[PDB]
Image (cartoon, rainbow, N blue to C red; front, top):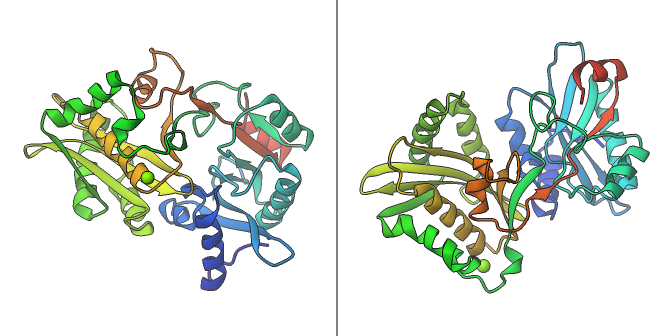
Length: 335
Ligand SMILES: [Mg+2]
């Protein structure tokens, strides 16, 4: 069925399923629609014979150069997507709710790529975008398919971040702290401003645009201090670097960062160490450091993130598209 966002009780059940699901994703939580307040929310779900929710999908509709909308369920749906018969059922509900207004329904779940899975999806009528598309550009995928994920369940005895790494890396992580760097965290307006100052500075230094502060304020208003947390690194009164991490489902996700120009005393390493500590203290299964463009020392994102994740980067299935309007799809989507 389709979720009535005006029914507190219905909404409560939807959230309770999302928050308790091992497949939960913050970008599938109802709070995400509040962050993306410029998009239109349309959410659906399936129930079992007991009337209990077994699958859900939070979609957001965006405008395009055409009379059709772009329906996107970021990192959804919430369920075991390899169970394609169930997926088809959930999708059919989504399709019904979209009511012909969208030219496509796209979802990019965090499930490993495999020829077997890719083939099944294609056999079921879906159009997939992964190893067959451009690694970048407006034709690339919305979310990076390659991601540096730290699997903490491999270290059941880990008490502190250092316990996860070899001596050489322990050295790199100890450096900033040994040099006076200190990190405090929370989710207050004060910490958001601190983040914003480093965020805009880093953006200017990199010649890129930055999201407005209101974006993060909506995020702060949507998620409590146990879900969203900002880490601020400083040295003797000098703001150095920051990072924003979200804890949801089976992982804590390093989503945004900022760092001042000049000498930063490896403050970014300190931020990472504290985010990882938060994962450990909360018994979280995974710490996700985000995407990379390529697994090579030529990728600076890979270089930084490889310090904390020595395992191979995870490669997801990519974008799964349920083509609704063929003509428009071919116009707006190409390899
Ligand atoms: Mg623990």
